[PDB]
Amino acid sequence: MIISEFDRNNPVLKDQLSDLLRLTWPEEYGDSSAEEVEEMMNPERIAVAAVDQDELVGFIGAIPQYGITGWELHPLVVESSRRKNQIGTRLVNYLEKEVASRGGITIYLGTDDLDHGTTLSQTDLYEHTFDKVASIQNLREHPYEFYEKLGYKIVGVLPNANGWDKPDIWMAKTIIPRPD
Amino acid sequence: MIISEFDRNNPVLKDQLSDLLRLTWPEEYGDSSAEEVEEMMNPERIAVAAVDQDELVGFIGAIPQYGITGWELHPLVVESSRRKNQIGTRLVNYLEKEVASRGGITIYLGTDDLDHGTTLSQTDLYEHTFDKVASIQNLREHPYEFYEKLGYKIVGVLPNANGWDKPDIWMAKTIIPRP
Ligand SMILES: CC(C)(COP(=O)(O)OP(=O)(O)OC[C@H]1O[C@@H](n2cnc3c(N)ncnc32)[C@H](O)[C@@H]1OP(=O)(O)O)[C@@H](O)C(=O)NCCC(=O)NCCS
Ligand SMILES: CC(C)(COP(=O)(O)OP(=O)(O)OC[C@H]1O[C@@H](n2cnc3c(N)ncnc32)[C@H](O)[C@@H]1OP(=O)(O)O)[C@@H](O)C(=O)NCCC(=O)NCCS
Image (cartoon, rainbow over all chains, first blue to last red; front, side, top):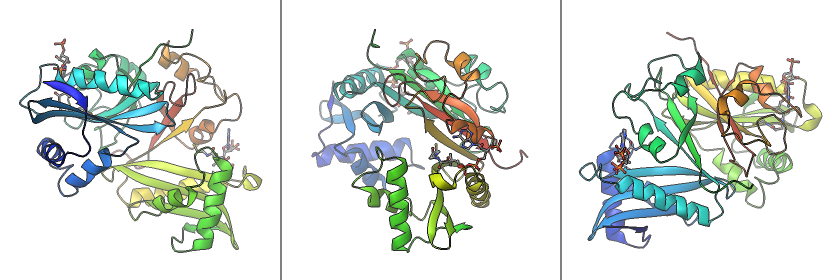
């Protein structure tokens, strides 16, 4: 299958994206699902799709949050039935090329830990904040490790973001060579 | 000088807010300044202002970003001629109370360093990241210290956010006692 820029004018494709988002995150994409999809189609954003034949199996987007330099990776979803076969890796790498081409320097993201997937949850993060970040361990195949393998680093945490001891984990990667 | 809920239907107050935002952050607030002000009026957000008889002297807002438990403090501004008189402190204190009333647990913010205002800028933040964060110093009266004095702690940094060696500094505070 191929990874390419998402055709913002393809009703069918946009429908599959909506479903994929609703299925994956039913609590986050219930009503305004097709609506948030349109939000992801914004010209200022980047929208990359993974299509097998004619089926959308993965999608990744990026939002410019700091001028043209800092972008937020959001969202990233791969059909639960097509995971573990480099689709996510290929989507992230394609996104990075697209961001760089627009003058982007860094991409960051927030990956939450709501069900004790890592050692950063179920603990007071204001205590030994960064020692805990540095010694993080993946307890339940939390996706933060997916990003680490792609070169992203945990650069921060948001204590009790989603409720007591259910933090958001901030990760980032600078995608181009540093002026030398 | 009464710090209270911002009147979201007052067009004149909104124009002053728009003005204050363009004077404080001319790079972030330009032609579409009125639009950005309307976004701050969204029903889910908290909007609080310090008003002296008729002049808008300060404004603070908050956005629920994680359910209703995690809120981003944005924006916060006090007229230059009125600073260092506790108006900022009072705006934040008032906001924290209102956020808590709405179910908030944590308030966070991102304060950028674009002009070597702290030791975190003008250096490759990917080398000894947390060592540098741990020994941060305030070089040009950067506002991160204002938040630190109010109980906020640096919980993260985004290297090269605004361009090489011009990071964003993430700070946060849990506003209610831990059960
Ligand atoms: C996380 C996700 C996007 C990864 O997509 P994918 O196509 O399955 O990932 P890939 O096959 O490209 O994985 C590449 C590498 O990352 C690792 N990896 C992937 N998901 C992982 C996880 N949850 N925990 C640990 N490692 C993981 C793989 O083992 C592989 O490592 P290896 O090369 O050493 O074997 C996908 O599983 C998904 O859709 N998850 C749910 C959505 C989500 O929570 N996203 C996080 C955004 S906040
Ligand atoms: C940052 C700002 C809101 C502070 O408002 P303020 O009314 O001047 O703050 P206060 O007078 O309540 O300050 C309380 C304490 O913080 C300190 N403080 C305030 N601004 C500070 C700064 N920039 N650097 C260091 N300390 C600062 C005060 O000295 C005082 O300390 P003390 O209690 O030890 O005497 C104001 O300067 C402002 O509007 N700045 C421009 C916009 C901005 O940068 N906003 C921050 C968003 S990231």
